[PDB]
Image 1: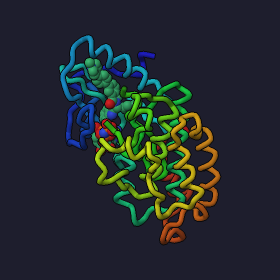
Image 2: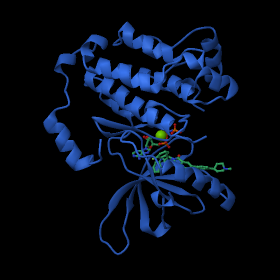
Image 3: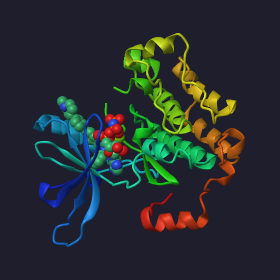
Length: 292
Ligand SMILES: CN1CCC(c2ccc(-c3ccc4c(c3)C(=O)N([C@H](c3cccc(F)c3)c3nc5ccccc5[nH]3)C4)cc2)CC1
Ligand SMILES: Nc1ncnc2c1ncn2[C@@H]1O[C@H](COP(=O)(O)OP(=O)(O)NP(=O)(O)O)[C@@H](O)[C@H]1O
Ligand SMILES: [Mg+2]
């Protein structure tokens, strides 16, 4: 459906403030000025690294239409594109940022309820991408965006190097499947349970494949019970077909989310903020009106 990707003019939007960069380009906080109107609508804008040719832009558009066609509460959708020399991409602005920075800044105030619900939502989004036959290839806490504290969405999928998030067969044989995404999901969960720790911190990326082949894995986070750690370890099995399926990950984390303090051991957990019905309805009406 071509109607899901809006082709924008350079003159109808403006970059306002840089937000960061990653690997494909630089992300800005921007404003869309609807023509003939007086309003300023905040947007996110990604300007590509290098300028491109009409041929490479066709490759861009072909993938852009796919990323504009997703429809799931836990998966971000691409909204627009500006075909300038350097192409500019447009999606919804998430004022809370990515989940990695969120858990790092709130590391002393995040309860077991939020952590397990984030795992559920990430698996729900990943299960949708598999249903659409879309391989993520870059699943990580940095590519999980926070719309509201109770609602996260996965982003930056389908962009065919994050060595420390890749499955062993991706490092060794550039093999990317939905089962290699499960490995990245396991590392993503590890990031959340360590409140944003860098996986294999201090180990050179050139040696990661060596340590994985000989049997070493990311260590058990201090707040994790053995039940949670064994899920992460199953995501990191050498046989890709032995790793759990995302639909299985949804069920298992939903079970643990029903009794969070038995599976996560967090200091002050009984004193952390729970999602209130009053808070969730307020958040929805102001920032998050989608179906759910
Ligand atoms: C020879 N030459 C090699 C490279 C070249 C090329 C370059 C770029 C894209 C391409 C095409 C399309 C997307 C991306 C990137 C890319 O990074 N995207 C993110 C994405 C992915 C999935 C869902 C979603 F909502 C967003 C994203 N982050 C944003 C942040 C702010 C504003 C807009 C944003 N858009 C979408 C494809 C091919 C073509 C051939
Ligand atoms: N729609 C958005 N709303 C708010 N912040 C965003 C949005 N898209 C991206 N960002 C942020 O912009 C910064 C740069 O994003 P990006 O260029 O994708 O880098 P990255 O995610 O760190 N690297 P990569 O793994 O390649 O995607 C990060 O801090 C993102 O969280
Ligand atoms: Mg990203």
